[PDB]
Length: 299
Ligand code: HEM
Ligand SMILES: *[C@@H]1O[C@H](CO)[C@@H](O[C@@H]2O[C@H](CO)[C@@H](O[C@@H]3O[C@H](CO)[C@@H](O)[C@H](O)[C@@H]3O)[C@H](O)[C@H]2NC(C)=O)[C@H](O)[C@H]1NC(C)=O
Ligand SMILES: *[C@H]1O[C@H](CO)[C@@H](O)[C@H](O)[C@@H]1O[C@H]1O[C@H](CO)[C@@H](O)[C@H](O)[C@@H]1O
Ligand SMILES: *[C@@H]1O[C@H](CO)[C@@H](O)[C@H](O)[C@H]1NC(C)=O
Ligand SMILES: *[C@@H]1O[C@H](CO)[C@@H](O)[C@H](O)[C@H]1NC(C)=O
Ligand SMILES: *[C@H]1O[C@H](CO)[C@@H](O)[C@H](O)[C@@H]1O
Ligand SMILES: *[C@H]1O[C@H](CO)[C@@H](O)[C@H](O)[C@@H]1O
Ligand SMILES: *[C@H]1O[C@H](CO)[C@@H](O)[C@H](O)[C@@H]1O
Ligand SMILES: *[C@H]1O[C@H](CO)[C@@H](O)[C@H](O)[C@@H]1O
Ligand SMILES: *[C@H]1O[C@H](CO)[C@@H](O)[C@H](O)[C@@H]1O
Ligand SMILES: *[C@H]1O[C@H](CO)[C@@H](O)[C@H](O)[C@@H]1O
Ligand SMILES: *[C@H]1O[C@H](CO)[C@@H](O)[C@H](O)[C@@H]1O
Ligand SMILES: *[C@H]1O[C@H](CO)[C@@H](O)[C@H](O)[C@@H]1O
Ligand SMILES: *[C@H]1O[C@H](CO)[C@@H](O)[C@H](O)[C@@H]1O
Ligand SMILES: *[C@H]1O[C@H](CO)[C@@H](O)[C@H](O)[C@@H]1O
Ligand SMILES: [Br-]
Ligand SMILES: [Br-]
Ligand SMILES: [Br-]
Ligand SMILES: [Br-]
Ligand SMILES: [Br-]
Ligand SMILES: [Mn+2]
Image 1: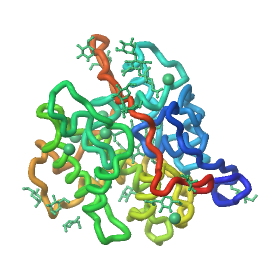
Image 2: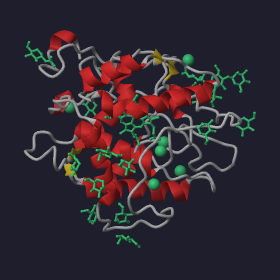
Image 3: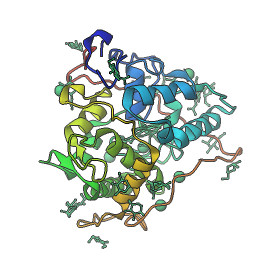
């Protein structure tokens, strides 16, 4: 928000306004990175981004501690080298390359289509990067009519997404990614669980309106009473949440789940790509921005 607005105070005392991305700006498949870039906490153009820029942006503007993004930073830079064909040093070339498929970006996302979702021909691909309202609605529908949801509900959401993606993706494309997705499950609980409830740290419940605002608008739900978690969330909370989601009892089982879907997941680890492997072409679509309604500087 505008620095003088005081909207972030006393949690963020140095805010910057929302600015929609333009057609030449680079955006990510990540709702967090996109919100940060929209506010210029990382470059508005989404290019040439250092590790410390990311660390400071998450810590000071989203209440996400450095520990939470340690692996994510490692993996962003691995993917940058893989996509561009050279070491990116400490300047992430852009945000868009993070949508390189079957890498950091993965199938069965909560709010993005898959790279080969619903394509008639094997060589074809689609926008697996920009926010997709219909896809997000498939996630939200699992918790329809509710204001909050718990670990068991999140487990049902990711199962629904896995089922739909396994059915809809071009045959042979779909690849399950429980470890990376469920770190992101933990990220959702870390950012938009309801800290106004007495037992939030131990038994976090996602506020659906906060989640929907963050994903749809790629800006922060201050108007709904959200603020950056204080103290900043640490990696322990995230991986504990991740484990809790996957441990939760499944009471409704979708059909067409991949083998072993129900059950614990492997620890997320650094990515690696063979030097022989050429990257998949990136979707070239202009960056998404909210238009129903468009957002003001304080939204
Ligand atoms: C340098 C730090 C980060 C990097 C490089 C990064 C990168 C990515 C990438 C490549 C994806 C796409 C995965 C997919 O859905 O296919 C993604 C998704 C996601 N990210 Fe980030 N991320 C970072 C930090 C964070 C943080 C701190 C949060 C929240 C606390 C967050 C929230 C999410 C969520 C919820 C998704 C899933 C979106 C969906 O499934 O529709 N990210 N991120
Ligand atoms: C973010 O950075 C990535 C990585 O540099 C950009 O993707 C790459 O964009 C270049 C065009 O600048 C593509 O190069 C072209 O490739 C074709 C076919 O290989 C070739 O015939 C052309 O002569 C040219 O070299 C490259 O393919 C593409 N990389 C991938 C894996 O898709 C991306 O455009 C950047 N996005 C933004 C919004 O800045
Ligand atoms: C991205 O751009 C490529 C050429 O620049 C196209 O070949 C791709 O199909 C893809 O097109 C989509 O996004 C661009 C914006 O860069 C639009 O101009 C297209 O209409 C399409 O939505
Ligand atoms: C914001 O400023 C107030 C008043 O000086 C201060 O008490 C508070 O700690 C500040 N918040 C942060 C995150 O520094
Ligand atoms: C997006 O932000 C606008 C402006 O604050 C708000 O009116 C709208 O409800 C938000 N969208 C969602 C889905 O929360
Ligand atoms: C989440 O899981 C990690 C291991 O992946 C632990 O280090 C952390 O304490 C939490 O249990
Ligand atoms: C790890 O931490 C999470 C979040 O605090 C808990 O919900 C979980 O029960 C475990 O203690
Ligand atoms: C990972 O951690 C979660 C949260 O404590 C557990 O529920 C799960 O059994 C696994 O050990
Ligand atoms: C069984 O219970 C789970 C978790 O409580 C729900 O998510 C599911 O919809 C079913 O009712
Ligand atoms: C749906 O069905 C699966 C196995 O078919 C169970 O693992 C799950 O708990 C739910 O009953
Ligand atoms: C229980 O919930 C699952 C996942 O949301 C569905 O696949 C199933 O049809 C039932 O509604
Ligand atoms: C979230 O984190 C937990 C604990 O490391 C994993 O079990 C899960 O697969 C996901 O990566
Ligand atoms: C990471 O691991 C892969 C193996 O999948 C290697 O190809 C790569 O060079 C790096 O060591
Ligand atoms: C990268 O590009 C090569 C051609 O140089 C393909 O063979 C490969 O499958 C990938 O698209
Ligand atoms: C986004 O832009 C529209 C104009 O199309 C305004 O009506 C709105 O207030 C927001 O700034
Ligand atoms: Br670029
Ligand atoms: Br489809
Ligand atoms: Br609002
Ligand atoms: Br797994
Ligand atoms: Br992994
Ligand atoms: Mn994805």
